[PDB]
Length: 63
Image (cartoon, rainbow, N blue to C red):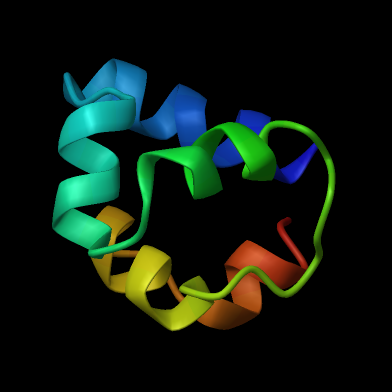
């Protein structure tokens, strides 16, 4: 699921939830919630896209 896609990229990159949430500028809770499969449109999607240097298209769709 989407949070996996996000995470596994960060992991390889070296980043984790804290660094992620910071760089995104979201709440730490929102990262867990992302990994709770809770929301397709999280309140930082474009911000996440910049955070992993991916597109919004890819984040939503995803290969």
